[PDB]
Amino acid sequence: QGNQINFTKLYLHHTPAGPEQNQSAVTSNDKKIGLGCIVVNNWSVYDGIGSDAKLVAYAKGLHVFAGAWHNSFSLVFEDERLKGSTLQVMGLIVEEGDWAIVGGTGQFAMATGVILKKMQEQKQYGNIIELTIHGFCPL
Amino acid sequence: MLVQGNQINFTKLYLHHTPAGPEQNQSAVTSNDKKIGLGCIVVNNWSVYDGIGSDAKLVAYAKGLHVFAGAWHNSFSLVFEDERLKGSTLQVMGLIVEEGDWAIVGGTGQFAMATGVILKKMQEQKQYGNIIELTIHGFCPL
Amino acid sequence: KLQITPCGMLVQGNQINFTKLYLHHTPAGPEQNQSAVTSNDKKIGLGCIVVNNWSVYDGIGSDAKLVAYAKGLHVFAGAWHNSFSLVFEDERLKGSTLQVMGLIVEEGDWAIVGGTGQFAMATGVILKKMQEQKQYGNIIELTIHGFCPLLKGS
Ligand SMILES: [Ca+2]
Ligand SMILES: [Cl-]
Ligand SMILES: [Cl-]
Ligand SMILES: [Cl-]
Ligand SMILES: [Cl-]
Ligand SMILES: [Cl-]
């Protein structure tokens, strides 16, 4: 009938360059049209900032540049409490704005909600994005 | 039990699907495999207008991709441009570009957690593209 | 025109009741039904995109009637992430689709993220169980659990 979501703040490592690069462009923009670059991403997601943070999930999917980045990815949890579960995520922009939680699996079967993105830290080779998960699942 | 929300009905939107020509608004970045007959991937930034006439205002973009798997499977963000609806999106997924239906699989902003369908009907067939009438039927929980 | 109308929704309004389906995942051979169209980046270990038109049957015998196709793509980002339309063939179910998205082709689970026609607003999951491994592909058993909500109020 309704159960909300019990997360703290997550921090996604969006790293396009450097020796820890976790995404790759597989097509280029059409120069005439101004779109078409497709990037495939395996973004690590941590439970905090700093060397003591634990990796709790990966964001595995793709984003395509259609004048802005459209995303589709599986948020696959690795921490023991949620291992076996995913949230399915889709929407616009990587580093700010919102994404939609369009479904899920495991403990998140039938999840619906949103993920709010805020810039947390800009590093040399990438950035860290604060994720705030709001949503619910039916019981 | 029940989830309080708002049913959302949006009529008379017109999507400009323009594969070619000076107003081309999508690009194929892969080709169909010769032997299997599938594989073309097209990235699209389709404009969506509030009317068919000369005075129609652009009110959204459909930003995403579609892939040819014997028919075209679509995944995109319908991003609204009205300073009113600014930022808010509907997340759209499904088969066929010019006819049939798409699923509304989620949303953001004023359309957070949207669920529903988009109905497509071709309105005008032109030399380099077509105009597709869209009808949105959706529900957003509060 | 944008019409915003107060309404109620019951999620368990209409359960999606199917029998078991059987998906044919065939990467090679004379019945190959998918193609890889981008390459993995060797430096990063990800990037390959495959476009698929998987056939789906209602049984494992020769008299199994094809009832659907799974039309979409999967992308390798350390694991295969899937996005496809499940397009049904039979009359009454003609035109109707389930929208499916999630990780892994042959095991685990997928989300039902939406639908059209009779499956408008579908929500749920598809469980995958390996059913048979053949020379050019495998057959995957599909178990559908989900609901279509009914709207009320207004
Ligand atoms: Ca959904
Ligand atoms: Cl990026
Ligand atoms: Cl963007
Ligand atoms: Cl082609
Ligand atoms: Cl089509
Ligand atoms: Cl996999």
Image (spheres, coloured by chain):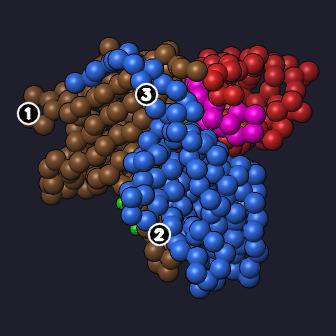
Chain colours: A red, B brown, C blue
Depicted B95 relative to depicted B59: above or below: below
Q: Chain of mark 2?
A: B
Q: Is residue B122 left or right of residue A39?
A: left
Q: Is residue A123 left or right of residue B86?
A: right
Secondary structure under badge 3? strand
Classify the position of ligand 4 by quadrant: top left, top right, bottom left or bottom right. Answer: bottom left
Look at mark 1 in the image and give the residue it sits on.
Answer: B54
Look at mark 3 in the image and give the residue it sits on.
Answer: C151
Q: Is residue B87 visible?
A: no
Residue type at mark 3: give it: Leu
Residue extent of the magenta highlight: A101-114
Secondary structure under badge 2? loop
Most distant residue in the left direction: B54
* Ligand 5 neighbours mark 1 (CB distance < 8 Å): no
Give how far across and how far down residue A94 sits, in percent.
57, 30
Look at mark 2 in the image and give the residue it sits on.
Answer: B38
